[PDB]
Image (cartoon, rainbow, N blue to C red):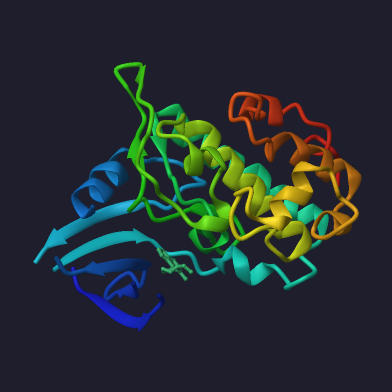
Length: 247
Ligand SMILES: NC[C@H]1CN(c2c(Br)cnc3[nH]ncc23)CCO1
């Protein structure tokens, strides 16, 4: 059936000639084989749906999110109301639990890859950098460096191998920091970085931590933990106090 390419989104918005259903089409001219492979395993309300692909230049048919990206809900230097931040983080955690549940790591979690549907539901998007980190119940450590510097965990910069799961968790905390303060805390989690050094020294009277409430800030203290082995895990995030706070 015929789809009209209405407009460019980033990827183009497509509308069905008969049903008028909307979808998004990723157009890549020749990573991609794996993107498709991974997309074929994914079925979750907090992950962008994969409809299919055509090998004409390659076409990926992906759920369309009229809400836009999460960054457009963050007023620079301000953030967003705490109740919206929490809801998005709840949904972000649901998405991430699912992926890790079937052994997949996104590896590039950031507001540019968190989309919103019409009810403002968050959808994890773009599995171009994603990889399988558990297969046949065996975990594989990662050694390739992927992601975006401000959202990347510190072990990815100093260690030759690392666990996939705590990396995604760190990035979710960076995203949470952004949702509540409108800014990113550091350019990268390296010790040459004054800002990351200040955090490691508990100077939370500076931004972005000054703008964050003590309850959500206590959770960030647990996520932005340099030792990936001491870093909080997702099941324990779900028991955190701000996480379960009525807002
Ligand atoms: N802002 C990052 C995204 C926004 N994009 C989308 C938008 Br906007 C809405 N739905 C989509 N599905 N897949 C991607 C996508 C296209 C790629 O750029």
